[PDB]
Image (cartoon, rainbow, N blue to C red; front, top):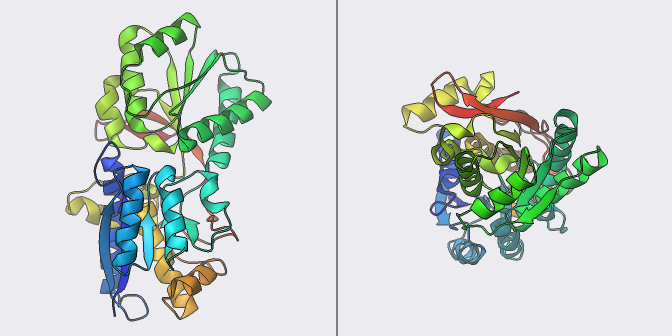
Length: 348
């Protein structure tokens, strides 16, 4: 019988673009795995669930997945969704592998079922904080976060690392997700002589801040994390996005092994940027571990994930005892016009 695998993601709402990356990546991997004979001879059946980046709607999705006989979940995107959802999964025989949720808490609760193909924010903040000290040692830095455990958690990790490396911020502020007028904050930063904004949060608020800062005459460079890696950032921010910096893993679209896969996505009308191949890889890890376990039981697949190594679009993947992957670390990107004339993130 079919192996039922769910995609839990923000298919609508502010982060819909990231939902699309996750859906498209997982769907293509399922198609490719099915074409090669499925998982241990069984076809994959995909079910979708839209969390709208809202923890409450996320748990409704989790419940739907349980009811529908889901065995594996690729998702979610937001740590604030994935963390509560993973408890439902853990208590109901479901393995969850997130391609994008980076809050350390996700894999620090001793749950049997939690895995990622992405990194975590203690690693990410360490890289960013060191970068701030290395390149902007003398700058007046504002640390701003979106008041979520993800955003504030990332800002706090970065603050710790920067502080240790000799950079003391002049401002530390929280804003609410969904708020869109930042003029008062921007004015405060101007008066404080801020030239660097570290942003702990996602692309919507980031693009708004970038756009408004430029309009209000604040010359500052925004630096963020992997929450802003979408074309939509440039759509919101406009040309002001140029020079923006952010941390992210190595770009998988650039791996030689993935050239055909990337061309196939584009032939289907999708640009497989950012988390698309992280989602693809999550599916590959599940299939790989199932093959090694000789079983599609989530508990057995989880054990196998923590023992072996498996081929993926991210390169050969293996997992530590907590479910975190052993893959290349974070690097800094800068936003510049790419060969196709569009602003995007390019590794420095």
